[PDB]
Image (cartoon, helix red, strand yellow):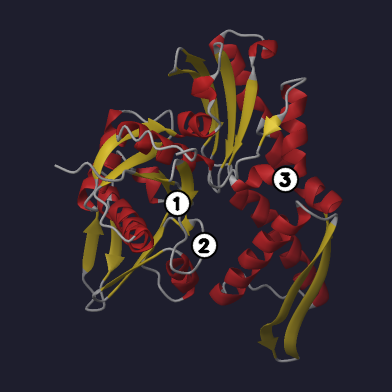
Amino acid sequence: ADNGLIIGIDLGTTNSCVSVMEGGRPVVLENPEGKRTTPSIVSYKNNEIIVGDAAKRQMVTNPNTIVSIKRLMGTSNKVKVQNADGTTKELSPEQVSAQILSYLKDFAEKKIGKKISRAVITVPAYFNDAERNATKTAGKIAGLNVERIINEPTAAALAYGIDKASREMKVLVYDLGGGTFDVSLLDIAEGTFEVLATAGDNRLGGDDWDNKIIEYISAYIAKEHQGKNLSKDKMAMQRLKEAAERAKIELSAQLETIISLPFLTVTQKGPVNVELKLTRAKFEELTKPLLERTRNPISDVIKEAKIKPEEINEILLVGGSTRMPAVQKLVESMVPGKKPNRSINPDEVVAIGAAIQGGVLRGDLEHHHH
């Protein structure tokens, strides 16, 4: 019976984001640790479910941490967590996904100062009915009336206002997430979106670029400390993953970065301190195979849609890793003449679009001009 706000949620494989319309503009809401996105990670302890940044950090000590649950959505697969009494609890992807949604909902309410019971949740364009219905159910479990499930590339196009275009547009969306890569071709006409073709690689994402930096640091460690290998040291590995992420981010702004890992372990010889330079050129060399794998899905969607690349009017970049300068160059190489758009934060653009759709569903005509 609610006529209230409809939040927009990007429930990603790797990270999630929540946005809402406020005074005729979409606003991205920060979680309680001040972050505009939240890891799509849930961990389990006795009488306690931990979501987001904290669950990620506690991975070192908690083997009952569930990552990438989106990959199982729409399946009858279960995940297992081990209770302290030695018994096993089976969880559905819906139940785990609901914990993520519940967390987003809870902090959004505290931000907005209002109870929230309505959402738009985004999904990949290739999701079938089972996968869509699983997402709806996760929403229902979290106490959300899921007003609409919309496609992630469609949400991105909504954020850029492409539905308002004066002519029919074909739009390419290049979506490089944390663990998956997706390409979509949309046709937008008379205000409605049609997915013409999709392609991708579900085992290619930003994490893979990070992993090359982890490998690079690990090679250096072995070379400088007589073959020393920390692959089994979970806290060391967590710090290397964190260091790799930071390095990658800095190399999107600068031509070099310093990886700094004081006191990474202690051997019989003494503390191990890593201080290591990585150039953008070397980072690009190490990861060129990953980047080149993004080329083939673009050619595939163009082929499938039966268009010439000149028929693509507009390109959207989605996913934080699209900030890498080498990604921009690749995409430009494949769609000559066109600017890869990332002026809306690619980490946030899908949730923003979902929030816009929420305002539309609510018939909210409040504008910043009023």
Q: Which residue is mark 2?
A: 35
Q: In the image, residue 253 lies at what x, y percent? A: 78, 53
Task: Pick whichever of labels 1 and 3 is earlier in the sequence.
Answer: 1
> Image height check: is 272 above or below 246?
below
Q: CA distance from mark 1 to mark 2?
A: 11 Å
Instruction: Say which of 140 and 70 sits in front.
Output: 140
Q: CA distance from mark 3 to mark 2?
A: 21 Å
Quadrant (top left, top right, bottom left, bottom right) of the N terminus: top left
Task: Pick whichever of labels 1 and 2 is earlier in the sequence.
Answer: 1
Quadrant (top left, top right, bottom left, bottom right) of the C terminus: top left
**Labels 1 and 3 touching (C-beta < 8 A):** no
Q: Secondary structure at mark 3?
A: loop
Q: In the image, residue 327 lies at what x, y percent? A: 72, 38
Which residue is pictured at 65% across the width and 60% down the height? 245
Answer left or right for 284 relative to 125: right
Q: Which corner quadrant of the image does residue 278 belong to?
A: bottom right
Q: CA distance from mark 1 to mark 3?
A: 20 Å
Q: Which residue is mark 1?
A: 16
Q: Tag 1: residue type?
A: Ser
Q: Which residue is mark 3?
A: 324
Q: Secondary structure at mark 1?
A: strand
Q: Tag 3: residue type?
A: Met
